[PDB]
Length: 48
Length: 250
Length: 73
DNA sequence: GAGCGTTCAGCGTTCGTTTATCTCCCCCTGGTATAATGGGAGCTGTCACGGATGCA
Image (cartoon, rainbow over all chains, first blue to last red):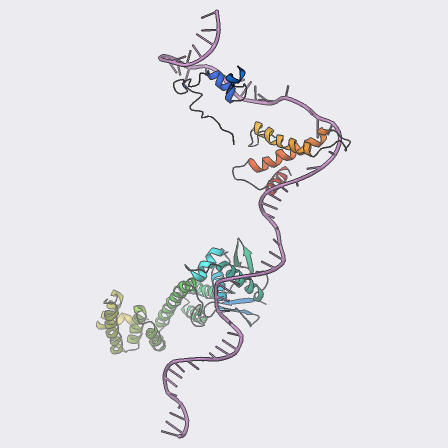
């Protein structure tokens, strides 16, 4: 019903997770396990 | 009210001497298939396979249920139990089945032989053979009944061969030749019956007729199978040819 | 009801379903607190789920109530 | 022809069949009305090596 994330590709050595999104592993632990929010998108043009 | 069952001829049942209407051929097939397990439950799969084999009708299971219900109307309540989705016959007294009655007499006869009571052993075998009211499972359709006809028909012949040996051992040669001529006509390929006949003929002094028995048999087995008689028949032939006195002493 | 083949956090979530049931069937016309009404529904949801989800080979709910009854006696 | 001799015949005559009806327990679901309102709990000590990851 709700998507999940592969344990292999994140939560491992940084040659495989890779920082493909510029986020620390502590940052990732907070967002995907429902402890902190992320701003997935901003209407930066609207705001101006 | 004592139920008795007959399977050594047409499938029959009696209650207090009155003959019960065992029904259609398929019901006799079902009853025989249930009687021969001696109280062990037969699953619905085994009963379908017993009646029709590899080609059952698409609604065969409902037919089996119909036959089972009708047996409950003629048999006493509680003998035909419904268990594990199948049926079993329970609560019969010991020896209520003639097959069991025939089997019990045969086991006692072996003990009587081991105890040396050949006269009682002959009588026990005589009482046993009288239970055959013709062809076992006569007129009963289905593949399962077919296997029992051959298996139990052979067993009758095996008991028959043993009785003649005991009769011949007591010197009753002259009576045995008459019955054996009918038996060899019905069972021409059974070499053991011809072995007993030739020995009986010699002890009845009919050596020339005994040798005549060898000549047709040797030709007949050559004609149908191309085979010589077994060594046991050959040695017995030779002992007549050697005029061995040790065959005539009981 | 922890330590019976169901994880402790899993028990909370199933009981949580019982709570949302209870509020739809509760009203002020009865002169009683919500706490007394709720606990019946919480216990119902937890014990039914325990019957329906603990064992690898599923056992029907009425067989389950039979075996724990005979076990206690 | 006498008297009975074999063998189709189609016809009944219900018994043969499989196929159609119809009555019953496991199994699943819903519901209890005093008040009850944030876990137990099991750990711990090998050893070296390296590279990520934190922080003075």
